[PDB]
Amino acid sequence: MRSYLILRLAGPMQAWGQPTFEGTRPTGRFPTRSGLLGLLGACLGIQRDDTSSLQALSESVQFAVRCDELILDDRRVSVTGLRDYHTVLGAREDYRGLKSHETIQTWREYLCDASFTVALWLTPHATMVISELEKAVLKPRYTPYLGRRSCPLTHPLFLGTCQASDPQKALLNYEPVGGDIYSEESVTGHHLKFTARDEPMITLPRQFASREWYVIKG
RNA sequence: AUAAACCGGGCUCCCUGUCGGUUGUAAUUGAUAAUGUUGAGAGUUCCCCGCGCCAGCGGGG
């Protein structure tokens, strides 16, 4: 009924953010909407000031994220976390001019042993088409990463392309099956939702608005 | 071009000094490896050269 694009986000370390104005940079357990929009953005070489392109992207695309557990030699490996005592010396003291602090400190959280399968699709008011997105994910223009730039991908961003009625149905065709799914679209049997502050307010730089995921447990 | 980007946790530091593991102790007694057997036959011994009366004879490997 609808055509989906299927991506895999997998690497030794990932980081998907939560509200902070502080030096500790938190992570949640799966990709944020903002972040996925950012990933696609990087693929479609969109500069940071290009509010038109950013808005087009945001209004065109929607995501569903599945949390894939890792299995090594027939054993399950749970997603764990990591805190990096991250230091900066010679950091700007102010936005104007060149005075700087001897040392500042930050704490940054990462996800270890995490892997995701993402399904994205187009909205009825789409400015784009899926062929574009596929081409981009296969040949990105800006460097693609998993949250932070220090976080490479260990598997091609492109997984596949297909067609179904649910996101759930779409994702069924792609191993590993069995993980939880967080979708921007409702799936009939399922009633639980999960609140986040993912949604980028493109008109207002680096500020995010509340939204809700639909949860499809496995 | 993702709470993103830009982005060291970083400098200094003997584990050091003393110390027998030592005295005593048969592995010891018994035990055929024994019966039986032509090495016969068969001139192939591979290469080069000389002489040949084509029976072979000789030189060198």
Image (tube, rainbow, N blue to C red):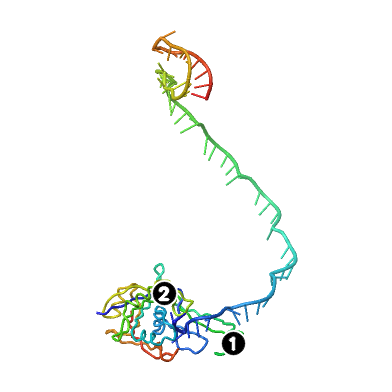
Mark 1 — on which chain does it sit?
A
Give the number of the mark in front: 2 or 1: 1
- Compared to residue A112, the image places residue A51 above or below, namely below
| Quadrant of res A130 | bottom left
Tag 1: Cα neighbours inside 10 Å, few (<14), some, or many (≥20)? few
How far across and how far down the image is residue A210, in percent?
Answer: 39, 91
Q: Position of residue A37 (x, y in %)?
A: 39, 83
State which quadrant residue A132 falls in: bottom left
Residue A85 visible at all: no
The quadrant of the rendering that contains the C terminus of chain A is: bottom left
Residue located farthest toward the left when viewing the structure as drawn: A1
| Residue position marked by numbered label 2 in the rendering | A10
- Residue type for callout 2: Ala
Number of marks in the rendered image = 2
Q: Which mark is residue A98?
A: 1
Quadrant of res A88: bottom right
Q: Which mark is residue A109?
A: none
Of callouts 2 and 1, the N-terminal one: 2
Say above or below: A121 vs B57. Answer: below
Name which residue lies at 41% across and 67% down. Answer: A73
- Under circle 2, the secondary element is strand
> Can you give x and y, in whole percent of width and height, for residue A50 in the image?
42, 86
Judging depth in this view, the residue of B17 and A185 nearest the camera is A185
Whether residue A132 is visible, yes or no, is yes
In the image, what residue type sits under mark 1?
Leu
Secondary element type, mark 1: loop
In the rendered image, the quadrant that contains the N terminus of chain A is: bottom left
In this rendering, position of residue B17 left or right of residue A87: right
